[PDB]
Length: 94
Length: 47
View 1 (tube, each protein chain N blue to C red):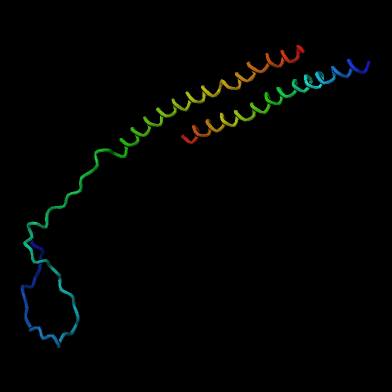
View 2: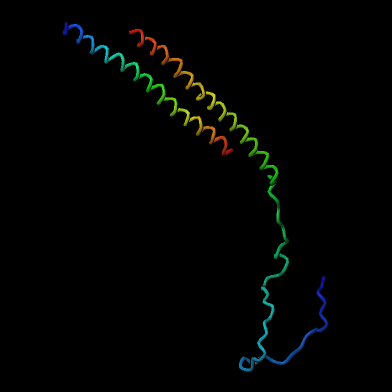
């Protein structure tokens, strides 16, 4: 698991003034690596398909209530013509 | 002559207009609830 590197180590001392050819070192933490713990990404069990099932069941349940309300409100036009026509005839009797 | 023949005119005008006032309620209250039904169907059409 060691990355390949031909060269071991080299040395020409670090005078703060004489910095030339500005490269950048690999910045590392001071803590032992063992707690830089492992990669884990876990799925939500509710799947893109499962939410489809749940929301479709909800849509189909709501459609029944919408149809119930429509059929409750679809009888009012029958009520108007069932209630007012006899009243119009009674007025006509005069 | 003019007494009884003009007295009945008030009731004539009342009845011949009460005949139309109910017709207006018949028409005006049917073109309004149909909007409610259309809105309900539109809401279902959103689903």
